[PDB]
Amino acid sequence: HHSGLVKMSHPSGDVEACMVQVTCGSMTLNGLWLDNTVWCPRHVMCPADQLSDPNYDALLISMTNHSFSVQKHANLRVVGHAMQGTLLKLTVDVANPSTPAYTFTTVKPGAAFSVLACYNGRPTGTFTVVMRPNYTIKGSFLCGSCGSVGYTKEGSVINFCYMHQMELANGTHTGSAFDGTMYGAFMDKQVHQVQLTDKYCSVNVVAWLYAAILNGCAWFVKPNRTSVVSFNEWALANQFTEFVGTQSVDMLAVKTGVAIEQLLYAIQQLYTGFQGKQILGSTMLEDEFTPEDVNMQIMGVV
Amino acid sequence: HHSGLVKMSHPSGDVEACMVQVTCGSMTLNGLWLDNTVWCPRHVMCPADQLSDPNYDALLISMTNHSFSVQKHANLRVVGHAMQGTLLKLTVDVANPSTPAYTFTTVKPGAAFSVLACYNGRPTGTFTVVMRPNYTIKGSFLCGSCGSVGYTKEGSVINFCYMHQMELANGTHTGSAFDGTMYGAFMDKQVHQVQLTDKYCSVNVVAWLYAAILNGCAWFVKPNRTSVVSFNEWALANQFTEFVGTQSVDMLAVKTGVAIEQLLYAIQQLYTGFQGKQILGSTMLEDEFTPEDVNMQIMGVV
Ligand SMILES: *[C@@H](O)[C@H](C[C@@H]1CCNC1=O)NC(=O)[C@H](CC(C)C)NC(=O)OCC(C)(C)Sc1cccc(F)c1
Ligand SMILES: *[C@@H](O)[C@H](C[C@@H]1CCNC1=O)NC(=O)[C@H](CC(C)C)NC(=O)OCC(C)(C)Sc1cccc(F)c1
Image (cartoon, rainbow over all chains, first blue to last red; front, side, top):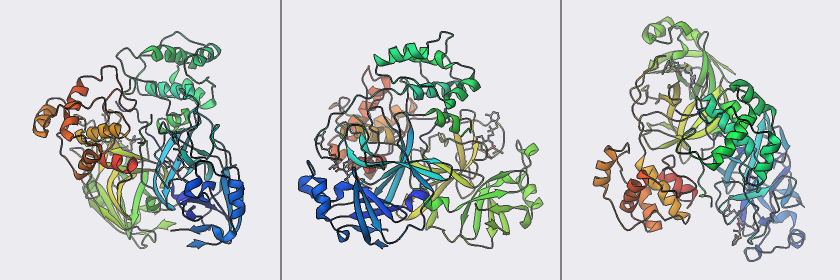
C-alpha cells in the first residue's frame, strides 16, 4: 500500500523567470534577478588559483561595474555592485518584469524548501530538500550549479531561503541565505571544513509515523507514552533532535486520535530496531517528510 | 556519504502555462491547452451518480459546445468537442500563445516522467515518478487532481505521456496517454479493478547499484557474473522484470569498470538479503532511479 507521500516541489515557473547567468571573468554561475538587483555567489570574482583562500574584500575592490556580465537566456548592464556576506548584490538598469511577490527568509533544520537547479543561467531541474541539523542538504548539485536558489511558497509569495555555494566531502551541500550568511559554521572557501553531526529530525519522524496511521499502518502504536521532556533528554544521547510540537503536528494527532507522546515512545523503540517489520515500506525511520507535507499531500490541508 | 541522487523533476514553467480549468456541469478538473485544443479527462461529463458505470458515448452526444467551460487563472469558448478513448478533445477559438514545442509519447515501465499536480486549473506541485510494471505510479494525487499531466523533456520539446484519471485501492495511481488509452488494463470507471502484480525494475536496480560504485560503495561487487538470459529466467520466478540493456547502462559500466552481469549476480544475492549491510543508506534494492538519472545527476551526462 502506497502512502501517497512523494518528494513534492513547488512549481518553479515563477523562479525560472528570475534566473540569469553571471560571469566575472573566467568563472560563470547563476544569479537571481529580482527588481533591479541581481544576487549571485561572491566567488564568481575568484580566479581559479585562489579558490582555496580568497580575499573577497580585495577582489571586490578590484572589480568595476563593467566587470560583471549578466545574461538571460537579454544581456543586463551592471550599474552597481556590492557584497553582503558571501553574496554579491549587483544592480542593473533594467528591472525584471516577471518579478514575483517575494520575501527573504532563513530556513531552519527540519524544514523543507524547493530547489531550482540551474546551469549557465538555464533551469535544469527541481527538487525538494530538508535542511539537516548540521545545516547541510542532501541535494543534487554539480560544477556550475552555484547560484541555484532554494525557496518556500506561502500563497503567491516566494520566500527565498538558499543559494548554493559548495559541496562537502560527504556528498552533501550547503549554501547561504540572502542575508549573506552561510548556513552553519561553513565558509565559502575551497578547503576541507569540519561538519557538524547529522541528527534525526524528531518532528519529521513523528509526521512520518502519523502518515502510516493515516494509511492503516499502526502496529507500532502502543498505549505507552513518553513525555516530550523525557524524549528530548533521550534524544540528546541518541543523535535525535529535540522535539518541539507545532500546530501541524497537533492536527495530525487530532485526526488520527494518536498522541504525540505515544509516537515519541514508539520512536525510542523503533530506533532500537524495526524487528523485521516495515512501516510504509521502510525498515528505518524517515525524517525527510515534514508535518506540513503529510498535512498537505494526504489530507489536503495547507 | 550522500549519493548525490535525488528525485529530480523537470522545470514545470512551460507546462504551467498550458494548464486550464474545465467544468462540464457539477464536476471540475484540469485540462491541457495546446494550440486550439484543450485535452481533459472524459469523466468531467459524468454526473456524480453514474461514476461507477458511465456511458460516455451517450454522455458525449448529450453535450454541446456550450457544455464545456474552460478557464485559465481568461475564459475559453469551446468551438468543438470530440472524444478519443478516455480523453476529451475540446477545440477552442484561441490558441495558447505559450504553447511549447511538444510531442505525444507513451511511457514504458521503468521509465521516469515528471508530473505537474494541479487543482482547479492552478498548478500546485511537481514530482517525478517511475511507471511501474503494473502500469501504475506511486504519486501524490487527491480529489480534483484529474487532468494533471505527466511529461518528459528531450531538449526544448516536451513529450506529454500521462494524464491522471484515477486512484487504486493500494494507494497508487493510473492514467491515460494522450491517444486515449489508459495505461494497463484499467478503465475510467469508479469500480474496483484487478491490478497486475508490481515488479522490481531490473534496469533501474542495476543503475542504482552503479551509482553506489560511483560513490565508493562497491562491497556487493564480486567477480562472479550472471548472464542476462539466466538472470531473466531467474527474474521470472522472483517478481523481477526481465533486464534489457541500454546505451545508458553501458556508459555506467564503462565508467565504473564493472560489468552488468556482475551486478545481475549481485541483485540475485542482494534479493536474498543485505545481511546487515547497507547500500546508499538503504537495506533494500531501489528501482526508482533510472540509468539516465544516474548518468545525469552524478556524472552530468545527458
Ligand atoms: C559552484 O561554483 C560549485 C558547485 C559544486 C561543484 C561540485 N559540486 C558542487 O555543488 N562550487 C564550488 O566549486 C565551491 C567553490 C568554493 C566555494 C570557493 N567548492 C565546492 O563546492 O567544494 C569545494 C570543496 C569543499 C570540495 S574543497 C575540499 C577539498 C578536499 C576535501 C574536502 F572535504 C573539501
Ligand atoms: C479526479 O477526478 C479523481 C482523482 C482521485 C480522487 C482520489 N485520488 C485521486 O487521484 N478521480 C476520480 O475520482 C476517479 C473517477 C472515475 C475515473 C470515474 N476515481 C478514482 O480516482 O478512484 C475510483 C476508485 C477506483 C477508488 S472506485 C473503488 C471503490 C472501492 C474499491 C476500489 F478498489 C476502487
